Image (cartoon, rainbow, N blue to C red):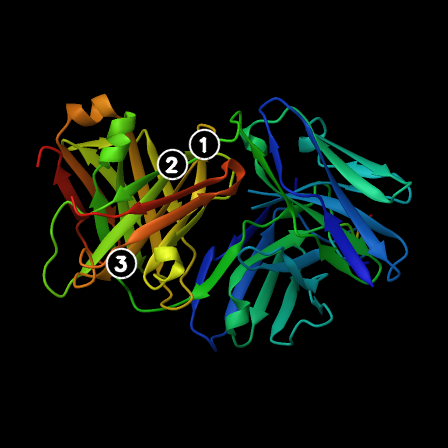
Amino acid sequence: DVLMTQSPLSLPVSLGDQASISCRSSQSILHSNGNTYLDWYLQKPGQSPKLLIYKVSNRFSGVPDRFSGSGSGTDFTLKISRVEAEDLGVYFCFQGSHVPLTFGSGTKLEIKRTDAAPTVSIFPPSSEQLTSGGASVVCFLNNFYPKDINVKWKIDGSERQNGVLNSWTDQDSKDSTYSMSSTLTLTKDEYERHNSYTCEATHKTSTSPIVKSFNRNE
Amino acid sequence: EFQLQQSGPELVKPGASVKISCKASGDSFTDYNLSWVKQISLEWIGVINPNYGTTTYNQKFKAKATLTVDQSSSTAYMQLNSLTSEDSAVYYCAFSSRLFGYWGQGTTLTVSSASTTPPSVYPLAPGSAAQTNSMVTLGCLVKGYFPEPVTVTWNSGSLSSGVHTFPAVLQSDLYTLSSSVTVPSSTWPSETVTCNVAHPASSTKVDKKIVPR
Amino acid sequence: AVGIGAVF
């Protein structure tokens, strides 16, 4: 198969910045008929991908001229001369020359803002849930930037990984931050077996883990 | 005119099969073909030319997918066989012609052994009291339901600033969703904060007031 | 030809 890779995977920009996204194929995308079926797509959240550039450098009708494509063979580049807000989203390159047709992994064009430390909140199981027989501990990590964050659960000081469900929001339209929810689900017996429950976040805004805990018996 | 229509969301049990559809209509094109693309990350499954019935597959999907055409109605179909959780995804139909292409809205497929199951709604209240002039974060945990969607609001939609509702996640055949809301310490608990959860498929409506522990 | 299946 022809493998397509994009660089960078994440591209934070300010509005008005120039943006460049590259695509490399493992074999040449030039078809024997002379055409190079290299396309560029933009996908906005909750929407279908939309064609921007086809066959390396042809702007599809209606696509603004701030978008341009170049390259040949195995190396291709999409350029945005001046990024506008409607441009934010995930960009995919696509090769349609060689079966199986393949896509790059995508590049997220996002808004750059100042760093923001997460607001971390931890919650014990509700009495409702305990009455029903289960025990979930919840940790919200809210309104942070940049988007890269890692969360670790510790029970009585030991890391726990089974029973964890994580969910992430898209970049906020108003303050350009990200948020994350982590839910550790235990049996009620397990919850009653341990006392100290800790949510630990690793984020660029602190050199040490950002910790929130509670003791069950308090 | 031009229209590209895909069939609606599908819920299927593991090991079962499903057949979804795509139709291009209008007076704006002659020859065309229809490709199927999977998104969990885009993957091309195959292509069918409805006017000739010719198909080309991604060998990866040769057993998993069968592309057909109902030439009576000009409707293309993709059958996905012997479903596993690997197959839960959005499936796009992508139209190609001499002068333009176009992607449909997508068909979501969810694989689960669960029948319709109402959610349990749990309040998330802080275990420690709040300092003066601080922000307090409350939450709502919505667990064990099927299928999507559940809806969550706060104070019947009158609490909208400072809300984060997190996308639902399917795990062990059931969904979990959560929602947080942040308010000044001077407003809770002195004013009530309630998460309102609705699950249309089970005709469920739950109001859970967040009370201090 | 334009679109995912333009080569066919």
Q: Is residue B40 left or right of residue B133?
A: right
Residue under label 2, please give it: B143
Relative to A216, does residue B132 appear above or below in the rendering? below
Considering only order in the chain, which callout, 2 or 3, is on the residue closer to the N terminus?
A: 2
Along the viewing direction, whichever of A162 and A21 lies nearer the viewer: A162
Q: Which mark is residue B182?
A: 3
Q: Chain of mark 3?
A: B
Q: Chain of mark 2?
A: B
Residue A80 figure quarter: bottom right
Q: Quick one: label 3, few (<14), some, or many (20+) residues within 10 Å?
A: some
How many angstroms separate mark 3 from mark 2 (CA)? 21 Å
Q: Secondary structure at mark 3?
A: strand
Q: Quadrant of the N terminus of chain B?
A: bottom right
Kind of residue at disc 3: Thr
User: The disc labelled 2 sits on which kind of residue?
Assistant: Lys
Q: Which residue is mark 1?
A: B174
Quadrant of res A40: bottom right
